[PDB]
Every structure is written in structure tokens, then in C-alpha cells.
Image (spheres, helix red, strand yellow):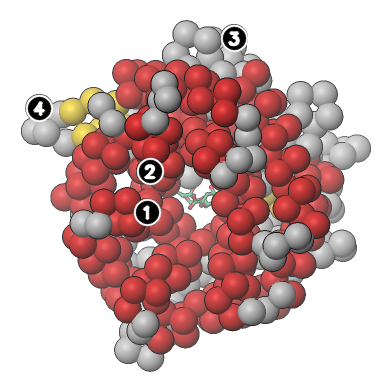
Amino acid sequence: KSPLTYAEALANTIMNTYTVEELPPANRWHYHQGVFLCGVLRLWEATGEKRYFEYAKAYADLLIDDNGNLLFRRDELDAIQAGLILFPLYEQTKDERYVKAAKRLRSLYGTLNRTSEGGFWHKDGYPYQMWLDGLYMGGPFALKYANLKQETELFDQVVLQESLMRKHTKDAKTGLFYHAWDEAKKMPWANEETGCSPEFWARSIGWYVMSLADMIEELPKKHPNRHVWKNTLQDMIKSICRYQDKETGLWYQIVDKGDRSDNWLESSGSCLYMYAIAKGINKGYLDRAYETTLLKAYQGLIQHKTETSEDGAFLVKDICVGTSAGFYDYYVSRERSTNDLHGAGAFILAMTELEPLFRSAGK
Ligand SMILES: CC(=O)N[C@@H]1[C@@H](O[C@@H]2OC(C(=O)O)=C[C@H](O)[C@H]2O)[C@@H](O)[C@@H](CO)O[C@H]1O
């Protein structure tokens, strides 16, 4: 069907599964709900259906009180991501509660611990460790804030975070990027010479390319990193696409090792690549010929990873559960779950960006 049809089916399925008080982890401000609700608000923009806006707003209002107060994990980049929902909520409502909450999250950057060259630790509990996922958790928010409040120092901050991750985790051979880097070389997964984790884990690279694809347009005009991030996205997408599965159109949990019998096709990473490829084409960062890769991914996604239940629920399966930096055997051993929120968010976002290219296919 058309991308938005599946996006609405998944969103309504999950909205029917959980009240906002249940949306897991329940009564917590966290990126799982933040990425799902980014999706639902994108869907609201695409369709104009107010129920999508209202559900997102109700989660925000569950967690943020009359004075803008919010409880969250104060050492985690992960806590910052859900702040992305605050910008459309504020824009629609002008309710200063949302800007107040946003400023609480933005104020976190100055409190977090850092590697020697300034890269944020993923959490206090992960000292000297940068994980690719954190570019999505902390980067787009910062640039939205920068534009809302005209704080150019946040442009500089995201430029630095990204350059450090790319400097330390990009593999020149494949062009893929390792999941995490430990400057201290204290974790068991840290390579003794480079500090990197050993594998290309699909979702983490997915968050990175989604981030680049979304952040370029938030930079000032003529900002030097417009060129840099475009170039970076182009090469990353070329690298990723080389590993697309020829039979299903999808990508593997461990991107470069799809021949391994204990590897498997994973949905959230695949949807993130679809998002970044569609977004890149839509914005002109990527050659339009990537549309075939994209539509092939779309066909396999639906065919192999989705279904409707006897009771009518739309199900996206084989989404990796929450996963840390680690080894091959740990990654391929991760639980494969259905309709997990970060994967549902990636699915819904992918569909909204795919919709225009689907509509115009052939023209
Ligand atoms: C420290 C630890 O491993 N905590 C577990 C959670 O992992 C953290 O949460 C996230 C995330 O997606 O929420 C991913 C990383 O694994 C890590 O930062 C999580 O895996 C959990 C089950 O949801 O169990 C915790 O013990």
C-alpha cells in the first residue's frame, strides 16, 4: 500500500495498545517514547489528524507539570531525545511549559562529563564512551534549540560531537562506523589500539545517518558543515547500500556479516536507512537513483517484517530490543521484539519521508 497507510496503521495499533500512562517505559521521559512520538507528530503534520497531535501532547503533559518541571535521567544523552517533541508542541500551542522543559534538557549539555577533546560520555555509567546512538539522542535537539533560541554555540557543539565520533569510529575499509569508542580503553569491547567496539551494529549507524539527514537543514545558510555532513551522508549511504540484502531489500543486525547463519535481518536499522535515504533524496543530498534501493527496501520491509493480526493489529516484527555496545555474539543474541517503540518510531518516520517519493514514482 502507500507508506502513510502503514504508518497510520502502526501508530493507531500502538495508540490502541497503550494509554500514554502505559507507553513504555511507563511514566518515564525517555527516547523510546520520544522517537515513537516524533513519528506520530510527523504523521500529524502529514495527515492533519488531530488525534496524533493529542496523543503526543498527552504524553508530554503526563511528564511535564504546570510549571514546566520534568523528571528524567540527568546523566543520559538518552533523556534529551524526547525534547524533540517539544518544538512542534510549542509551535502549535505556544504553551511556554514546553520551552521551559526544553530549556531544562538543553541545560544538561553543560553538566555532562566529556572525553578529553570534548565528546559527551553516553552516560555517567559509560565513562569516556561515545556511542553513535548519542548523535541522534543529543544532536538534532540541540540544533532545534539553537534555531528556536538563537544560540549559535549549539551549532558548534553538534559539529564537534559529530566530528569526534566520525574521527574515531569510521572504518576506512568499509565506510561503516563502529558502534562505540572508549577513549579510556577500559571496556572489554574496546580495541586496544583504536578504542572502538568491534562490530557494525545496524541501528546505531541508522541513528547516525538519520541525524545527518535531518540536521543539515537546521544549520545557518552557508555553514561549513552543510557541505561536510552532506558529503558524510553520501559516503555513509553508499557504504550501507552495498550491504543491502539482495533477496529481501533489508539490512542485517550486523551490517557487514549477512552471510553468517547466526545473523538476521533487523527492522529498526532497516527503517532508519530507509528514512535517511528518502530524506536525503527529498532534500537533494542524495542522487535520485537511490529510489530503487529505497523501494526495494520498502517492498521487503512490508512483505517480510509486517503483518496484520487476527484482531487487526498492525505488527512490525524483528525490532532489536534496547542494546548496548559489545561483541558480535552479544549483538546477534539480542531479543527480536514486535512493535517496540523505537522501531515503531523509525518505521513511521520512514513512511512519512517515503510517501512523496512513492507518490511521484515513475514521473
Ligand atoms: C546498564 C544496562 O544494561 N541497562 C539495561 C538497559 O540498557 C540501557 O538502556 C538502553 C535503552 O534502549 O533504553 C540501551 C542500552 O542497553 C543501555 O543504555 C536495557 O537494555 C534494559 C531493558 O530495557 O535493561 C537494563 O538493565
- Locate residue 117: give its quadrant: bottom right
- The reply to whether dot 2 and dot 1 touch (C-beta < 8 Å) is yes
At x 68%, y 26%, the residue is 238
At x 29%, y 56%, the residue is 44
Q: Amino acid at mark 3?
A: Asp
**Residue with the mark numbered 4:** 310
Give the distance between the C-alpha atoms of the residues marked 4 and 2, in whole angstroms. Answer: 26 Å
Residue 161: image location, x then y, percent: 75, 58
Q: Quadrant of the C terminus?
A: top left
Image-based side of 47 in relation to 300, left or right? left
Image-based side of 2 in relation to 195, left or right? left
Q: Residues within 10 Å of mark 2 (few under 14, many from 20)?
A: many
Secondary structure at numbered mark 1: helix
Give the distance between the C-alpha atoms of the residues marked 3 and 1, in whole angstroms. Answer: 36 Å
**Residue with the mark numbered 1:** 42
Q: Is mark 1 within 8 Å of ligand 1?
A: no
**Residue with the mark numbered 3:** 259
**Residue with the mark numbered 2:** 352
Q: How many marks?
A: 4
